[PDB]
Length: 153
Length: 153
Ligand SMILES: O=c1[nH]c(=O)n([C@@H]2O[C@H](CO)[C@H](O)[C@H]2O)cc1F
Ligand SMILES: O=c1[nH]c(=O)n([C@H]2O[C@@H](CO)[C@@H](O)[C@H]2O)cc1F
Ligand SMILES: [Cu+2]
Ligand SMILES: [Cu+2]
Ligand SMILES: [Zn+2]
Ligand SMILES: [Zn+2]
Image 1 (cartoon, helix red, strand yellow):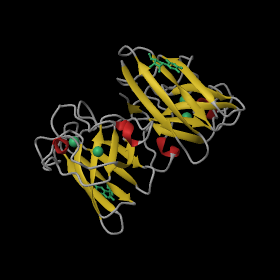
Image 2: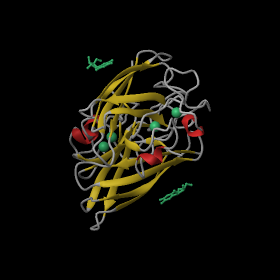
Image 3: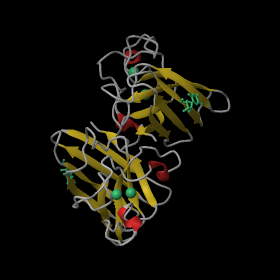
Image 4: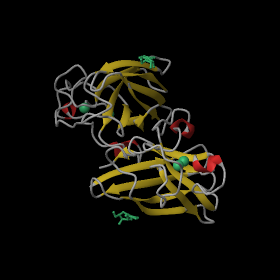
């Protein structure tokens, strides 16, 4: 198996830890962990293109989109590779994450390692919000916390 | 060209920004930036195996060593891929980094992207310290600041 990890931090109270595991080369990737400090509700959750945090999370650029597609949800054919949808926090401010995705990878052209995982201000509308920005970012707003995805033991 | 970047942070005052640029696939990598908050003198400077900062910089593991060599300096044949020697801080606690290295890469088996860059407490003795640990870590002590190396625009 191949494994990766990401520590999420930002300028505010949001922080977390997300693990990735890919049992077979090019197979599905399990994504699991926990994010705290969040407002109750949905928070967009994406791999962005660059692993650059020079100026904070903004330096990561747009969503990771090697195939030059429009934004969508993880279940959609038409999505960015980095489109992992939303995490959902309760009143406790915690989202307990447990996803499997078959588009992201820990190897090859769709490898997310060395790129930035971001948790966003508000909901990702999965490309269904009815403006041009929906089909780019999902209208998920600002970047509360982020980290560079790294190779794990 | 291929580019990468690393933001160095830790639990104390040490922080910095380091850029990587590789003009050609097989070719040397230029490494430059700035680190502040240091004591005067040498601080070991290495790429460590894992891009895992879960528990802080300790989580990054040993020096990156895809060839199972012993520890040395960047100008030695016998070195870990991750052996970038020392940065040197003046009285103001700033080290101004500008080197070139032919062993690290931003692609392939020698790829440092997705791994952790670390600045250490103490001098790296470049494997010349006369003890077993010298040829493993260079006796560079604890990890003052680190970051995961990410793909840059
Ligand atoms: O060794 C270097 N040091 C350095 O500071 N740079 C910076 O990177 C830019 C050029 O790529 C700026 O000219 C310069 O400040 C590049 C280098 F290659
Ligand atoms: O939500 C989770 N999903 C999950 O797969 N795991 C586990 O995933 C396993 C991979 O076989 C373990 O590495 C363990 O981290 C833990 C979790 F909390
Ligand atoms: Cu995002
Ligand atoms: Cu080191
Ligand atoms: Zn997207
Ligand atoms: Zn070494």
